[PDB]
Amino acid sequence: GSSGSSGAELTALESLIEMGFPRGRAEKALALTGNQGIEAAMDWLMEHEDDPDVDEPLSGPSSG
């Protein structure tokens, strides 16, 4: 951990981020769910916890 003071609620998204989650995901989830809430979003996340490609590569496999 680095920082963790006070416990506020910015937004359904931010809140998620507070869980150390990636924006792209949270956002995607929230959006996917329909910006309903965390629990709702999380459900998706947890489900996509093993997503095949939550963030597909934008370039291609170039060796390595």
Image: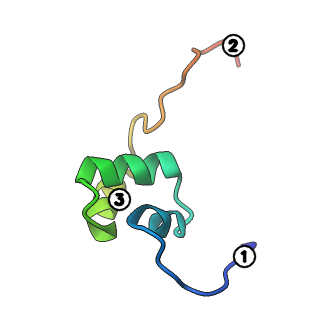
The mark that comes first in sequence, 1 or 2, is: 1
Looking at the rendered structure, the kind of residue marked 2 is Ser
Q: Nearer the viewer, residue 26 or 8?
A: 8
Q: Which of the image's four quarters has the N terminus?
A: bottom right
| Res 26 quadrant in image | bottom left
The mark that comes first in sequence, 3 or 2, is: 3
Q: Residue 25: image x %, image y %?
A: 44, 49
Q: Residue at x 43, y 68 (%)?
A: 11
Looking at the rendered structure, the kind of residue marked 1 is Ser
Q: Looking at the image, is mark 3 or mark 2 nearer the viewer?
A: 3
Contact between labelled residues 2 and 1, with CB atoms less than 8 Å apart: no
Q: Name the residue that disc number 3 marks.
A: 46
Mark 3: few, some, or many residues within 10 Å (few <14, many ≥20)?
few
The mark that comes first in sequence, 1 or 3, is: 1
Q: Secondary structure at mark 1?
A: loop
Q: How was this image coloured?
A: rainbow
Q: Nearer the viewer, residue 55 or 9?
A: 9
- Horizontally, is 36 left or right of 4 in the view? left
The CA span between labels 3 and 2 is 31 Å
Q: Name the residue that disc number 1 marks.
A: 3
The CA span between labels 1 and 3 is 25 Å
Mark 1: few, some, or many residues within 10 Å (few <14, many ≥20)?
few
Q: Is residue 53 above or below residue 1?
A: above
Q: Residue 20: image x %, image y %?
A: 57, 64
Q: Is residue 18 above or below residue 5?
A: above
Q: Which of the image's four quarters has the C terminus?
A: top right
Looking at the rendered structure, the kind of residue marked 3 is Met
Q: Is residue 46 above or below residue 6?
A: above
Q: Name the residue that disc number 2 marks.
A: 63
Q: Secondary structure at mark 2?
A: loop
